[PDB]
Amino acid sequence: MEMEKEFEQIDKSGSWAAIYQDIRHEASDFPSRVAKLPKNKNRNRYRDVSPFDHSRIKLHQEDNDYINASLIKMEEAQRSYILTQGPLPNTVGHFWEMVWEQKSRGVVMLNRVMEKGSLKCAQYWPQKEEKEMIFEDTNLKLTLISEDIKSYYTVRQLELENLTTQETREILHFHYTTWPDFGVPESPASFLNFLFKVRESGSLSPEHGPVVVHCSAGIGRSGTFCLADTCLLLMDKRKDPSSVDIKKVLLEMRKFRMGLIQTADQLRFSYLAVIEGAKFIMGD
Ligand SMILES: NC(=O)c1ccccc1N1CCCCC1
């Protein structure tokens, strides 16, 4: 069923809360035993948001390999994503160790450091060129190279140095700065423009490690970003673009991380983004 007609049918019937609970009921439940070990309590932002054991990213260290991060591998679309929480005061060094070890080119940030008067993630990148950061625990140095501030997003060029080997890499930081403190954006135009800027950079392409995507918990806004990207790529690849079922794609992605799309409003917004984005994919 053409999702645009499914959309109007749910809107006119006002059944978004009903569709959303059906997804919550059918979603996968896999163990997260490593996340719940007592040694890892200060590595988790939220007691109720944990990576599954089968899909968790492992740090390359014998001491403690744990980070709250999941590998989402979309087989038919040929896209992979790492979804992670906003870094905590004790996990900024682990965060950049993961970027280094997984060979990522891009980091996508969908939250502000402060929202609703509370801290949603640590200031984990340098704000001035002349004031770089050194993570002693993971032996990494991070330098701000350049910053391009736009009305709806900021793009930063960062240099990450492995102080052990003196290898360096360029990382691109894509920061969506205008998601409202409550609810979802009224139009998906700025969010789709932002998704197309990340794609244009090479950060989502198979010559690099997976993109790192985060918000505060790494499931809600982060879920909307990967769901919209994957659905648009499948509409490009398939003979019948109307065969793309957003609910089935979301349940596939929930095999790899719990709780993706946190509200019925985020589910409606994901449908709107895919419907409006398809009007480019199909030749406009
Ligand atoms: N070890 C670090 O993470 C670190 C290193 C250099 C400068 C700042 C740093 N952080 C920033 C956000 C979390 C608290 C402290």
Image (tube, rainbow, N blue to C red):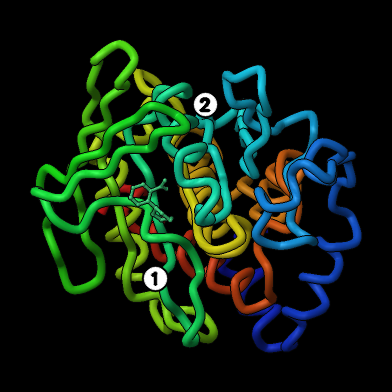
Looking at the rendering, in which quadrant would you find the N terminus?
A: bottom right
Judge from the rendering whether residue 265 lies leftward or rightward of residue 49; answer left or right.
left
Examine the image and state in which quarter residue 201 appears: top left
Q: Can you see residue 216?
A: yes
| Image mark for residue 192 | none
Classify residue 134 as left or right of residue 115.
left
Secondary structure category for the residue under label 1: loop
Do we see residue 233 in this rendering? no
Question: In the rendered structure, which disc, 2 or 1, sits on the residue that comes first in sequence?
Answer: 2
- Is 256 drawn above or below residue 41 in the view shown? above
- Residue 16 vs residue 236: left or right? right
Q: Report x, y in % for residue 16.
A: 72, 79
Q: Which residue is mark 1?
A: 112
What secondary structure is found at the residue carrying circle 2? loop
In the rendered structure, which amino acid carries the disc numbered 2? Answer: Gln
**Label 1: how many residues lie within 10 Å, few (<14), some (14-19) or many (20+)?**
many
Please say if 163 is above or below 253: above
- Disc marking residue 78: 2
Residue type at tag 1: Arg
